[PDB]
Amino acid sequence: XXXXXXXXXXXXXXXXXXXXXXXXXXXXXXXXXXXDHLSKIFLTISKSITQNPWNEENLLPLWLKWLLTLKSGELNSIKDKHTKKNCKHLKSALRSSEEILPVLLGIQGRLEMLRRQAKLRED
Amino acid sequence: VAVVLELYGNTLESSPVLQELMIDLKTKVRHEIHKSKEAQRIEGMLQLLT
Amino acid sequence: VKWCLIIHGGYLVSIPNLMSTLSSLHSTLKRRSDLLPRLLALDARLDCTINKFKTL
């Protein structure tokens, strides 16, 4: 309802995915995932997530999750011309974060290490 | 496990004991993930005293 | 291990060579730490099929 009208509007739109992103439901994220318009979603999704690896909203990465899990086979062969150039871009776009997730977990330890010694200064 | 997944996703939908085993394997893999988390954290925190 | 490192941290600052002392300790911490990307891969590897089957 919120997402179906946005799907008809993208069937002409990244603001449509941001506007159906006002729902934030995972069951709706699976149901609107099946209803090749999912590539018409992915053509905004791939660009928006490559432009931002650090977006702290959830429905665009979870929507990429439900798209890469629900549409896992056919997304490779929509096109081998112009989606896959961006696909060879996004492997570089994301795994930069994968390198520092061990380090970010390291400092995640290194913070509560000092939280606990400040609590020990309290007692 | 990964080659089993990419080969036998078509099998794993069909038998429910595979589904239950994948549920428990998900929990124990995430358990080892948090084990990896705590031993990553303790080694990173261990740099502070060095 | 955790509260040992919490309580005796200031003394453990004072000794210069910890990797002299905490070597097998560091080996255990790395040995669980090195398995992190394989497990992180396995999460998506499971969850492709997990989001495949429990709907249909």
Image (cartoon, helix red, strand yellow):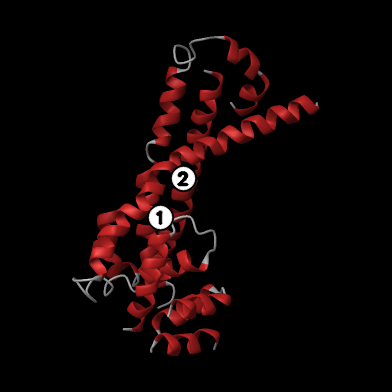
- Subunit under mark 1: C
Residue A48, percent from left and from top = 42, 66
Distance (Cα) linking label 2 and label 1:
10 Å
Q: Is label 1 in a helix, a strand or a loop?
A: helix
- Residue ID for mark 1: C43
Give amino acid for label 2. Ile
Residue at image point 46% right, 64% down: A61
**Is B39 situated above or below C26?**
below
Residue at image point 35% right, 54% down: A93
Residue A84, percent from left and from top = 24, 66
Residue at image point 54% right, 63% down: A57
- Residue ID for mark 2: B33
Q: Which quarter of the picture shows residue B11? A: bottom left
Mark 2 Cα-neighbour bin, 10 Å: few <14, some 14–19, many ≥20: many
Tag count in the figure? 2
Residue C50, percent from left and from top = 41, 66
The residue lying furthest to the right in this view is A123
Residue A15, percent from left and from top = 49, 78
